[PDB]
Image (tube, rainbow, N blue to C red):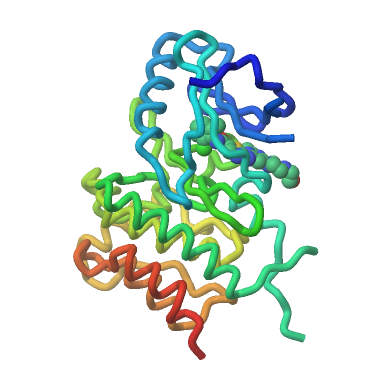
Length: 278
Ligand SMILES: Cc1nc(Nc2ncc(C(=O)Nc3c(C)cccc3Cl)s2)cc(N2CCN(CCO)CC2)n1
């Protein structure tokens, strides 16, 4: 149980619904991320905080954010993770351009490595029957040497990625499989569908929102068209950097039937091995 006395708050990194995240130095320089309660925290927030600790303490994988420590015994409450020095993957990738064979660059096999790491992380969450429910580049963190960690969740930079109706759950409908949109059904199989969208983002180098020229309402109609199965449904197009082989893998992630979507083990295998084929 970590002593908050050895923490030195340096920068504010972001706000959540019940917490804010700061950069801190640890005198024992060593940089960590510390999430604390927001200044307006009600006791509903406190509970959701203590519950996040419970949930997060499960998570032990190289490509999942890890809980390094807690100050929970006495206030103030805090959560400690590694500090991912390169911020979220959406931001990060947006700052790069695909490497030119003939601004900062990144290579196609590096895009695969980034995607593979997300897959390996999700392969891990699958073994825990843990359903993420909001997998997207914006919720992936980036450390040194293109290391990726999936975050447990989460705030205004990406407001347009969520569909909001008063009294309803805030929903990332553009990353959601049709059965989630239509039936509220969230499974590892729909995490697989959102991974296909996330892989699409990575290949787009986050240059465009999924279905970015369709309205929310049309995205929701598109879901119903997967359901009615009369071939009218539409898909994300193949990104410029994406070979047809990788794209068909993407399309498998958007099979109407949950069963026909690839498992993450296979997604990993492909990204780390097959994808390197000419
Ligand atoms: C929002 C943001 N976070 C960054 N790194 C983080 N590492 C871990 C984070 C985190 O929240 N851990 C966590 C905790 C502690 C509790 C519960 C759950 C979790 Cl997941 S956040 C870096 C960053 N950068 C902005 C840009 N900068 C210049 C480049 O322009 C570089 C830095 N911005």
